[PDB]
Amino acid sequence: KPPPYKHIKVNRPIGRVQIFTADLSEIPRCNCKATDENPCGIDSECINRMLLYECHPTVCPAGGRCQNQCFSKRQYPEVEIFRTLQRGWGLRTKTDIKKGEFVNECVGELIDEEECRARIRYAQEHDITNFYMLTLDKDRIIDAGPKGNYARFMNHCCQPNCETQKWSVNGDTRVGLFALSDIKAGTELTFNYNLECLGNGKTVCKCGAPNCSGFLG
Ligand SMILES: C[S@@+](CC[C@H](N)C(=O)[O-])C[C@H]1O[C@@H](n2cnc3c(N)ncnc32)[C@H](O)[C@@H]1O
Ligand SMILES: [Ca+2]
Ligand SMILES: [Ca+2]
Ligand SMILES: [Zn+2]
Ligand SMILES: [Zn+2]
Ligand SMILES: [Zn+2]
Image 1: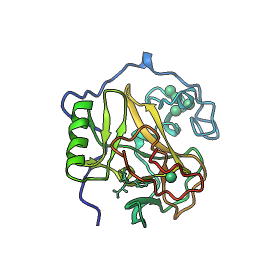
Image 2: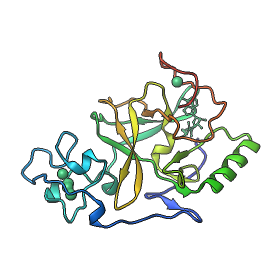
Image 3: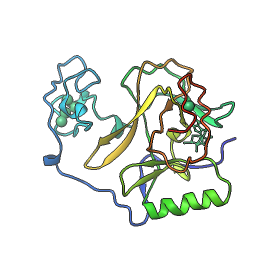
Image 4: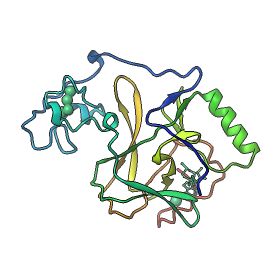
C-alpha cells in the first residue's frame, strides 16, 4: 500500500511563497471561432495554446466550446496506481491518450528554497529515497509528497511517453503533463525528470529503456 497523502486539487503556497495574479493585458487574445472544427484545440492556430497560455473563458471568442482551458477544467484521463518491479509505485492510464493531449497537473505544496532545503535534509538524514519535488521557478518548488494528486506516482524514464510544460494560467505558472505520443490504455505514464526534480542524487535509473543514461533525469 502507498503511504498516505492529502488529495488536493490546486497548489498550496507555504510560508513566504506567493501565488500571483495578472490582468488581461498580460494574456494574448486568440481569434478561434465557435464554428471551428476544434476551437483552441491541439491542432488549431490558437495563439494562446501556441504560447503556452490558457484562454480566459469570459473573453475567448470560441466561447463555450473553447478547448484551451485544460488546467482550469481539471478533466484528466482515467488513471490508476500499480506496483512496479523496481521503481516502487507507478501511474498507468486506463484510457487511450492522444499525442499532445493534457494528462495531468503536477499539484502540491508550493515551497521556497529554504523549505525545500530543510525537507531534503530531513529525507537524507532519515533514509527517505522517494521525492516529489518539481521546480516551478527559482523561487517556488512543487512538493506533491505531503499533499498532491495522481501525477505524484508518475515515474522517470529515459524514453518517456509524457513531458512537462510550463503554462501561464490566470497570471501565474502551472506545471502540466502532456502526451509526447499516442498512449494505449494499460501503459505506465512516464516523463523525463531532466533537471526539474530535486533530491534524486545517487538514485540508479531503473526505467529499463534501451537508451537509459543510468541516472534520474
Ligand atoms: C515522483 S515519485 C514517483 C512515485 C514513486 N515511485 C512512489 O513509489 O511513490 C519519484 C521517486 O520514485 C523513484 N523513481 C522514479 N522513477 C525512477 C526511476 N526511473 N528509477 C528509479 N527510481 C525511480 C525515486 O525514488 C524518486 O524519488
Ligand atoms: Ca482564446
Ligand atoms: Ca482568448
Ligand atoms: Zn483559440
Ligand atoms: Zn479558447
Ligand atoms: Zn533510464
